[PDB]
Image (cartoon, rainbow, N blue to C red):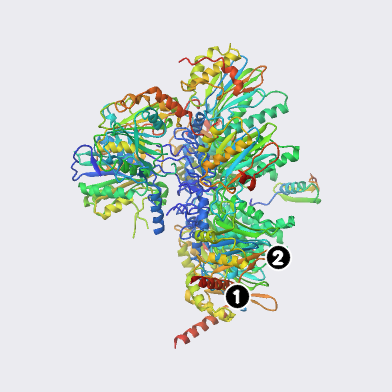
Amino acid sequence: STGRLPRVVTANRMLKQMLFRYQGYIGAALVLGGVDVTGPHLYSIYPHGSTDKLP
Amino acid sequence: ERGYSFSLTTFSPSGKLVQIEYALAAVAGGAPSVGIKAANGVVLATEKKQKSILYDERSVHKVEPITKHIGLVYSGMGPDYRVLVHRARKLAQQYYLVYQEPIPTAQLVQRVASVMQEYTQSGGVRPFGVSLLICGWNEGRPYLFQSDPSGAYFAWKATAMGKNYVNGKTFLEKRYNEDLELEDAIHTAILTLKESFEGQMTEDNIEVGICNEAGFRRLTPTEVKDYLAAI
Amino acid sequence: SYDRAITVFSPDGHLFQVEYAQEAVKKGSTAVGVRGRDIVVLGVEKKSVAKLQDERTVRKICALDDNVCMAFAGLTADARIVINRARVECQSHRLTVEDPVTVEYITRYIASLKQRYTQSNGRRPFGISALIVGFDFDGTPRLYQTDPSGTYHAWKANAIGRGAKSVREFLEKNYTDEAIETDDLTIKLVIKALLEVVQSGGKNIELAVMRRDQSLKILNPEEIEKYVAEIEKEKEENEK
Amino acid sequence: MFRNQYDNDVTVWSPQGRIHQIEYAMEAVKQGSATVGLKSKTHAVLVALKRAQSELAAHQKKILHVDNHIGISIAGLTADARLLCNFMRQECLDSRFVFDRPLPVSRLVSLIGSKTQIPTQRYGRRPYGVGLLIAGYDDMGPHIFQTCPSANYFDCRAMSIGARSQSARTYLERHMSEFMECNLNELVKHGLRALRETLPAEQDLTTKNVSIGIVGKDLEFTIYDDDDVSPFLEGLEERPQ
Amino acid sequence: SRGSSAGFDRHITIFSPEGRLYQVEYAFKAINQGGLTSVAVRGKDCAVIVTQKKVPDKLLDSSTVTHLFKITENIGCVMTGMTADSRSQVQRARYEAANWKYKYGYEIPVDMLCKRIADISQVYTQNAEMRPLGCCMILIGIDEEQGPQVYKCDPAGYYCGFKATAAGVKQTESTSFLEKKVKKKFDWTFEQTVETAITCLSTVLSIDFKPSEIEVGVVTVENPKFRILTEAEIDAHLVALAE
Amino acid sequence: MFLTRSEYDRGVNTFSPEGRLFQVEYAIEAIKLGSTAIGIQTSEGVCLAVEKRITSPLMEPSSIEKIVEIDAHIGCAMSGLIADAKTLIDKARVETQNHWFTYNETMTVESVTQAVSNLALQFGMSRPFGVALLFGGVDEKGPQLFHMDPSGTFVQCDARAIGSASEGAQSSLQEVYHKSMTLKEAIKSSLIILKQVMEEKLNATNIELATVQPGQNFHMFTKEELEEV
Amino acid sequence: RRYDSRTTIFSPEGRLYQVEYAMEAIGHAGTCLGILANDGVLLAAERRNIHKLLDEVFFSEKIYKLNEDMACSVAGITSDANVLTNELRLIAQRYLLQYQEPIPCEQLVTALCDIKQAYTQFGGKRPFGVSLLYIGWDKHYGFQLYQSDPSGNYGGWKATCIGNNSAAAVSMLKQDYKEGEMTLKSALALAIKVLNKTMLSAEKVEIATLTRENGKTVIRVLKQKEVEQLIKKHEEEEAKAERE
Amino acid sequence: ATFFGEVVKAPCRAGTEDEEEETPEDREVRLQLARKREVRLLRRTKTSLEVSLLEKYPCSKFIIAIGNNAVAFLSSFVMNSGVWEEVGCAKLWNEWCAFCVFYHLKSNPSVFLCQCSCYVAEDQQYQWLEKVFGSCPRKNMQITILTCRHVTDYKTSESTGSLPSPFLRALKTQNFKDSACCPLLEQPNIVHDLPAAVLSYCQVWKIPAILYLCYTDVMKLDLITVEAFKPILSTRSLKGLVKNIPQSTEILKKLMTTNEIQSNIYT
Amino acid sequence: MFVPCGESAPDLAGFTLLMPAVSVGNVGQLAMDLIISTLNMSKIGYFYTDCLVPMVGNNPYATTEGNSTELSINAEVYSLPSRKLVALQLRSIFIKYKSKPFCEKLLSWVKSSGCARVIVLSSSHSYQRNDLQLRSTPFRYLLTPSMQKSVQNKIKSLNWEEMEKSREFCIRIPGGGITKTLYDESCSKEIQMAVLLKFVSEGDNIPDALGLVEYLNEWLQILKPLSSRWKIPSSWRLLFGSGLPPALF
């Protein structure tokens, strides 16, 4: 739709919201990282829907 | 006489639906489109409606990709085309998620035509005033389909739609050959478009897309300029 | 000019769309029903016969349950819909409560379903009329009729469809207590009533028979022709 | 001749800026019998007239009971009156059940107006064809109100609605300067005199076609009918002519 | 509901024998009901919008009359047509931008906002209950990777990107003027863009302008926030043209 | 100064220029195609007399059930479109049974009347009903009689006549009726009124009576009891 | 007129004009033929999509397989026929899942005709302009052949025709059909003769047959060589007959 | 509109909706319907008159009452004295239809009265004209008509709810030499149906005639509406037929005391 | 039958007859009112038939206190003998199965009297126009084959548009009333006739009448050519009803 490569914050937002919707019953712990027009980013997502931005 | 011309859910005494004919009339007054299915490839071409220097050349396109191996073009009304394109992309993604393989061209055409058949059997809406040309590569074999405002689809070897499409189809009948290459197909498609341009043709007022075993892609204006110079 | 909408009254208090549905009923094939002491008979005219057609699929007599059967006149698709609904209702009721379904109960269900479709402008009524016969739990024969508007009554002998008035007049003249004494006499009465409007007897006449504690029986052309021959013989004897 | 296209629905404006269906619904009030309401410093009184049809086949209730301190009288369609009475009763009951305090008459009338304004702007509905006279007593004293099919209400000292109520209105406006100082008996007599002005000049009020309803500072809303009306009718004099 | 009206130009969902939508074409004519025209021009590193300001009543407070709106911090707008319809679309655009920000975590782009508005407008032309709004939108903004942007959408549901565009009563003459100027010269500085826009307006409408009769908004690369000029700045530009 | 057409009688939500709803009036006129019914209120009981018309002698004279009886000591009678009363009867029965199941006493005639009147007013089904009802019964207040018409509202009365020939029956009943009479006198009066209204004979297979009184429960007269009179 | 604008209006003589107008839409479609024999059933259709620049990427047109034991043919509006065929497949699969037995041939036809009747019963919708022919086999009645129309009616036949010029084909079938004494070869010859009269090349027809082998149903579509063989045999026998 | 998004057509003032869109069974139905609606002038022996009513007898005066209030007024104030013989009746059928009786005085057999309390539709008015008047009009005759209309039918510059009702209006032909007792009907207002037919017949055939109109706020049988006709009793046409007024008042009161039963609507 | 107001019928020979049709919007009737009011014609007789609903009223063209009390019926004939003009006016509508007899009787009278030609003012539904008609003038005309050559030359000079045929070819005028029947009978009886109509929608239709009367004046030249000129009759008041009730606004 947009014609551009995505941003890491979009993926982080979608994953966090979807994990939070199911109240931790899915049970997936993820390490997310990527590069976009604003530089490299790294996240940590927990099964209940909590995220941290760390080096 | 005119009693059966306004309602979409009303049959004529001779058993005809007239609003669908009028939607097809809307389609027939749009910009010309050409599709040619050659060996080892398919080509789609169309005429741009933004013929001015003020219009930006990278904002809105008429040739669109649906998947890595499926493309699209149209004649008729653009606003309906956008929503149909979005729905087609979503359907292809759903199929990939369920079956873990890219959707075939015929299945996508069937699903889109099923969406289009609705809006012709209910009161309070109007049919889509647009026709589509769909191309794809699948199992080492090219495809070319056309879908109507009523929801009916056909498989073609070469066709034209839009303004002056009868003469275009006659030209294609005279010129089309079974054992054709993709480059010759592009040449023939451009020549068919040139028959009714009514002006000077450049690379800034036509759009070309091709499909082969490497996937679907849209040609850059420099390639179109190189092709035009070879005529 | 008050006949364009279903739920519109005329200045003198009429609903014309329901009367037009009754008009649609009045053009079907004639159906006759007679109930006797221990037997109920149904007979239906066959309008036309095509040689390249399978006759099993165009019958106008059905069995709703083991103790009830029905004939109709009017549109055919509507009749099929109503028959399927009644059959499903009988099966569900029998599953829920083991008691056999009452003929009046199923008649009331059918009439309520028909009456539901004359209340809104977004749907049209059913253009059929039905004759329902059967035996109760105690063995008492019954006969009912239903209308497109939703009313129903109980009869001893009735006719519906095209050319029903002459058949009803004949039944009024000839229905006596000494004419329903035996099953053969009841069947002969039904055939004779049908013969007033049918061009050729036996050739295009369909007839069904139901006895107490027995399944529905469809008479064959041999038996129908035998009964017609007996009627012809007695008519010749009474000619003089 | 040019009104035929604009007077079928309530959601169509006329080229002159008019809505004819509301004006037509305002004509249904004049199909009922006349009724009169008036008030003094302490009491508020409603009097109603019943149709000359024999009591044999009909027991009409023109005056209804709403709460312990509110009563109404009707002129128009009966189904709309029933719906409005049910709504008012429910409102009063809910207010009493929530807070132990009577519902003010002005608030009740405002709620009624808000409720009846809605069907005049929405498709598939029609205005209410009923008018009401409302009598009540609260901390501010006695009140008389009037209600219209157009969702308008007025605060009155004396009002009359129904068929041939112009004579009653003329009498009320002619004799309106003495109502404050009167007692209950004089007030009821004035109401009866106003009501009987709507009859042909040979009939007279009897105990078969008159209803009376009274509320006051210490008197709850009560309805007098049939033989209970005779002590009020006995003192009335004969016609001037 | 109420029920459609018979005729080939009296209902939104009826095609004519030539396949036309006359109700959409009639909604296009409501844009000229206001009587005003506006011009948007894109420069090398800036974008401007100019529109005329008519205050016919002496008793009317002139500070409450405007056609320039702020959607987000970095997006500006100019509306032409029916006033209440324009204000309703401004509110809807703000709501859509808020939804995008909440859903995706970053600010919406100009082309995406224009596409969303056009998608919403397309639905009104296919259902029998709702009607199109008689107004057109023009948006400007600065893209992080691409630069200045000029976009426009119309009542039919069609949108596009431009280098210069106009709308209103005298759109055609402005389009011809801008086409000549663009075919002549490119690479305008910030000053030249405002000069070109004001010259186009003042030539299409044979008027010598006062600072109180026009309204100018700008966005630039150095300061990407949408800004509305003042009378002193407008008069400075006007004397710059005059000299 | 020209003559033109104008219509106001096609929708149920349209007002006439003189404030009339014509569809309701037409539905009321539809009642006069039914059979005559009589109801009389007496201090000893309530007597309901209804007319039964038979189109053909082949019709069974037992399925024409016009006097349906609801519980809690309540009668009924009907005239008009018979198929339209079933929903009203079902609502009345359900309401009464719920009252029994929740309180364990009898619901009042006025209460069941109001409850069934709520359902008849929902057309503002998309059309008014085409039937009229008459209610009877006794309570702690004594015997009561009520009447309903397709306008959807009830009204208390003590002697009412409904049906095709109702004006003459009402005129005769007004003269015959007295403030005090016996239940048998009321029954005889109803029978003579029906006799002089009917165009045919009055054997025990033409009428249907169900006299209700506080002594015992519902009692629809049998063939023998009817033939006695 | 005033009675032919909706499907929920009865004319004063009890007619539904919109349904008849819908059935008028079938006379413009291609011809479809069906013949029943002692050892098989037949389906012959006429190809309207004839053109030099058309492609052939499908199993067949106007002939569809519904399950292991049934097949159908359509005439009318293609976009409506697609919906109807999809619904038929769903109904058959649902019955198989619930009962663990294949659906009888008549129940499928009844279930689809209920759907077709609902769209004439309820207002605001448009009836389907499609007519269908069904062939199949089941353990209750053996080989079968049915027909359906836009109103929701159906019936069983031994030989029938729908589409353009149906009356002449029906007359010829009535004249030339022998009941209880025909085989698949005779049915093929009769179909070729009737189609030749009503409309010949192998590119304008399509034929499918149904048969039972070793307790298994076999559904086939004939080839160009076989169609040409049948056509030339008919031509030579006609010439031989007319030479005398 | 019976469903969402249904196309509908607007109504027409002129009625150009059935005349433009134009079988033995259909014609048989049409003739049967035309036979159902037909005016018959009987002698209730069950024999129709062979000729028109006014050709069988010589007539000098003719008074017609249309509606219920007018019939009540004439029965109370005019027919209370003298001997009147019924000489015919009219039979017809409509959706809204009740009697039509003709009398004449015994002492003076040249004075006629008619009392039409029924409603005559548009396709039966002319037939009424031939069955009553005939093809030979007599110019030595005088005709009077009385009828009532609702007050909302009157057109005024001010609100129609402020007019003092009932009030009376008149219309005359050219040959009428007397003067009405009430103002003539104002311009934009017109009259149609049966009284208009009678007046038009008289105007075309040069027969002096007058039509009286009452505009009332209650259309039921009401005493005020009936006594609104009283000023007509002093005219030359009705001078010699009224004898005793209090007896007429008593008869009117007795007639009003009996009235048919209305419905539960309009409490 | 034509019954005269006096004792002897007027002599009409070579007169031009103008007449409306009862069509959508009453445009022809309003135009006839405008013409009769402006030219100040005089009543000469009645057209008594059995085909129109009867109605009655006072003088619709009253100017003084003397002529304001003249009775009027649903069909009347006005004449202007100085310029040989005669006009018929209809003030009501038609009963069922009565239009064809009326047309037959009227054309029989026209033939027997001795008039030269007949001009009919009508109107047609505006929602049955196609795309080509949507962008053209709303005025159309028709002519019989028997019309004199001078009329066709003048009409060709005037640059008018002829009513389109419909698919042996026939003419259909939806919403025109008796216009088609009159045209067909006049064609079959060799009478010169012209039809002048306009595409209208129902509502307030006074500008339509003004446009139609100017269109007719372009050819007839009844008064001074165009380069407050038509008299509005005094009956054109309260066209929307009575006044506004109080306590509402």
Contact, CB < 8 Å: mark 2 with mark 1? Answer: no
Relative to H174, residue C80 above or below? below
Q: Amino acid at mark 1?
A: Val
In the visual, does G19 lie left or right of H127? right
Residue at numbered disc 1: G41
Closer to the camera in the image, I194 or G49:
I194
Q: Quadrant of the N terminus of chain F?
A: top left
- Asked if labels 2 and 1 share a chain, the reply is yes
Q: Residue furthest top?
A: D181
The quadrant where residue C98 appears: bottom right
> Looking at the image, can residue F2 be seen?
no
Residue at numbered disc 2: G96
Residue B230: mark in rendering: none
Q: CA distance from mark 2 to mark 1?
A: 24 Å
Residue H183 position in % (x across, y down): 33, 26
Closer to the camera in the image, E146 or D19:
D19
Q: Quadrant of the C terminus of chain F?
A: top right
Residue C109 position in % (x across, y down): 64, 53
Relative to D129, residue C183 above or below? below
> Looking at the image, can residue G244 be seen?
yes
Residue G110 position in % (x across, y down): 62, 63
SS at mark 1 in the image: strand
Q: Amino acid at mark 2?
A: Leu
Q: In which chain is the residue bearing label 2?
A: G
In the visual, does E16 lie left or right of F83? left
Q: Upstream in the sequence, badge 2 or badge 1? A: 1
Q: In which chain is the residue bearing label 1?
A: G
